Image: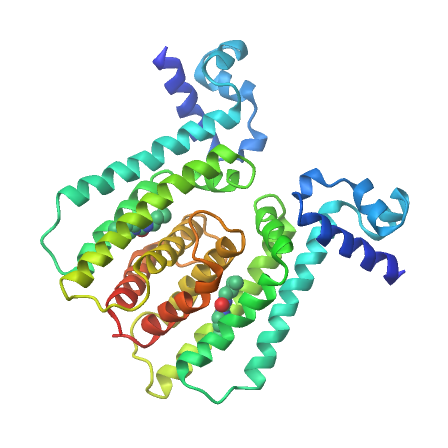
Length: 193
Length: 193
Ligand SMILES: CCCCNC(=O)N1CCC(C)CC1
Ligand SMILES: CCCCNC(=O)N1CCC(C)CC1
């Protein structure tokens, strides 16, 4: 039961490395998973649904990693603090490039994909803003822009920059340079006057 | 000749306010423009082509405005300098919200839309980096990150943040707050150590 569902999800992730979801058929997915077509339709209503579940797993992986970090603060300077946090997303999404790509493309066509992305981006922004607020309260960061609006722009920067880097879009920051680039912009904008 | 082409483009821009390109038919476009279907196909091979031409016009409008600014430097502090520049994009894309939305969505499905976007983003990044380099040469900005990589991340931030603001995505910066938010992040990251 969960065996064949997992195999469907694994097949989909493997195939999305090579082609977009549009050029992957339900037959392709069932064949890869060792099942028939109608047995596929037992587990998922559509190939779009498969991509939704893949994206849900990746987003929750990132979220759970960020929670783990928030419970286990590393003992470091504020630069390293933000770097370790940004790195959760760099590593988690960067380990699932094909899902990230296809998920971000689905936002324009799937309400459910858009909603998933929005839910988690709201959470991540809210947490960012709470950390900025804590830095301001302890006197380390100046009271400049509204923390939630600063957090929003920085999170959107990271989304667009990380995803362009992973896809080798032109233009993009090289993947080996993206974490230094983002961390600089976060630290200067959060702590600068 | 150019009358009916222009009418097609105007009809398309008006209809994309209400629905995505997928729910707009070639019949809808021809009807709005006062022409027949086969007369449409004289002027454009497809509705996708119409969106490409709309996006090309908006991108070149922004580009020409930025050139005009680069030839006519305002006499101001460095904050205002970047603000006036960012404002070119805020105003130009913000005056064509429906084209911006539909164009950005087409990037995932149209090679020609992706290429157009890439060409101009490369230009805008290169110009940003040249201005940063000039600020460093005159001693106003510190030599921190590679100027071109900083420019790339800041331009991608602006793309994602402006477009989320215009679309009222959740999450987004309110439109009335986006220019202050971006300018802060640009100034602190360019001039901060
Ligand atoms: C990939 C979209 C979200 C990016 N968010 C992001 O990198 N972080 C959000 C939360 C904090 C603390 C660290 C950095
Ligand atoms: C909308 C995508 C491009 C954003 N680029 C951008 O806002 N600018 C690029 C160029 C400079 C000088 C000002 C600001």
